[PDB]
Structures are given as structure tokens and as C-alpha cells.
Image (cartoon, rainbow, N blue to C red; front, side, top):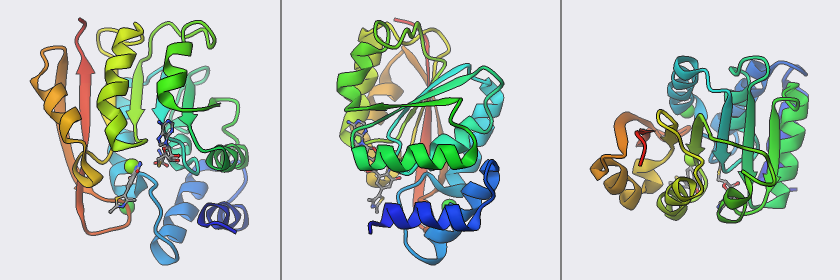
Amino acid sequence: DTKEQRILRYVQQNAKPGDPQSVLEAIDTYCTQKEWAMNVGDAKGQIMDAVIREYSPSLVLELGAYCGYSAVRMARLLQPGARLLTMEINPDCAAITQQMLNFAGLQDKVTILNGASQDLIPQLKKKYDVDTLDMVFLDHWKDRYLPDTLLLEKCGLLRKGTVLLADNVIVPGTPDFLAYVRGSSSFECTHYSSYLEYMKVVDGLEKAIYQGP
Ligand SMILES: Nc1ncnc2c1ncn2[C@@H]1O[C@H](CSCC[C@H](N)C(=O)O)[C@@H](O)[C@H]1O
Ligand SMILES: Cc1nc(C)c(-c2cc(O)c3nc[nH]c(=O)c3c2)s1
Ligand SMILES: [Cl-]
Ligand SMILES: [Mg+2]
């Protein structure tokens, strides 16, 4: 089996079905005590929680699902009727994410879209009936953050006040993305210094609020 399979099995055997907090705790314990994995983690997760609570987004787009940790973490705080779409290029990851969401009882709030973000983003309006996004969580691959941000703008998917939240702007680091949003009068940016998941290594999240074209 794979590490991702081991994480999922650990949750199924150590968390309570239908209880998202217990799922997060089981994942964080596994990744602390057994095998590191690239979930946003509890330290940066607490900052995401605060952002989600502040904005109460009706429609969130996540880029990069992995095992479903951030999807569980965000979806558990959404209001009734509010929705998450998560895009995931790796089908084995998409499979784990679906089972993780099912176990957590959050499957009615979240839709996994299978494919590369750069291929799916242009389909959101016509195929997935999206008008504009309230929030986007960027957590896929560092080199995609800037191009996908510009693609989301091109496609008309951002509105005034759309919240972009980006993980790993320090490690692995997204220097082109940070230079761009921080120099652009189309964004209002805030940096949230924290730590890499499960490690005493400095990392951070960037919040960039779109201000219109
Ligand atoms: N272009 C792209 N489109 C969609 N997913 C991508 C991608 N490039 C990488 N990925 C995926 O992005 C994921 C990064 S890890 C995601 C962690 C997750 N947000 C969490 O915190 O729990 C991986 O599963 C990888 O397959
Ligand atoms: C020292 C590190 N090694 C890896 C492998 C890290 C790491 C940490 C993350 O949160 C990530 N989130 C999304 N996508 C990634 O590629 C990713 C990578 S940090
Ligand atoms: Cl952590
Ligand atoms: Mg990350």
C-alpha cells in the first residue's frame, strides 16, 4: 500500500464516522507520529479556520485535494447550502479524498473535479454552472499559483472581494506569485506567518483579496 492508503485506513480505524474534527485529529496524529504528509496541518489550519469563519463563503474552490484534509477542514465550517469544489490531477488522490469526505459525512458539500486545474478552470462557468468564486485555496503546485490566478481572472471567475488564500508561499515557496499579488493594485494582500505542517520550519499563508480589474 501507499502512504495515502495508510492515512485513510488510519482515519477509518481511529476516527468517528460523521465527525470531521475526529478525522482531522486522526490525520494530524498519524502525520505527527508515523509518516509526514503534505496536508495543510493544524498550525496553518487554524489560520484557514479563522479566514473561513470571517468570510462565510458560499462557494469555495480548492486547487489540490491530496487525501482530503483541507477539504474536510474547510467543508466542516461551511454554512448549510454552501459548497466546495476541489480539483485534483492524481486519480489515486481523488479516490482517497472521496472516501475521506464520505467517512467525515461531508460528501454532500464537496465535489471532486478530476483533472489539472489549468484544464478544469476554463470549464467552471459552462460545464459546472459557476458564476463567480467567493474564495480560492491554492495548495497544488507552487509553479501553478500565478498562472492559475491569472487564468481565474481571464475566465471572469473572480469578483470584488473574492478571497485567495495560498499555502506554502514560503516553503516550498511561491516567489513569482507573491511578487505579483503584492505589486498588483488588483489585490489587497496579508501575510500569515506560521509553520510547515508537522514541522518546526517557518512557512506562511498569503491572503490576496481581489479588488476588480
Ligand atoms: N495542476 C494541478 N491540478 C490539480 N491538482 C494538482 C495539480 N498539481 C498538483 N496537484 C495536486 O495537488 C495536491 C497537492 S497536496 C494538497 C494538500 C491538501 N490541500 C490539504 O491540505 O489537505 C496533490 O494531491 C497533487 O496531485
Ligand atoms: C519540505 C517540503 N517538502 C514537501 C513535499 C513540501 C510540501 C508541502 C505542502 O504543504 C504542499 N502543498 C501542496 N503541494 C505541494 O507540492 C506541497 C509540498 S514542503
Ligand atoms: Cl501542524
Ligand atoms: Mg500545502
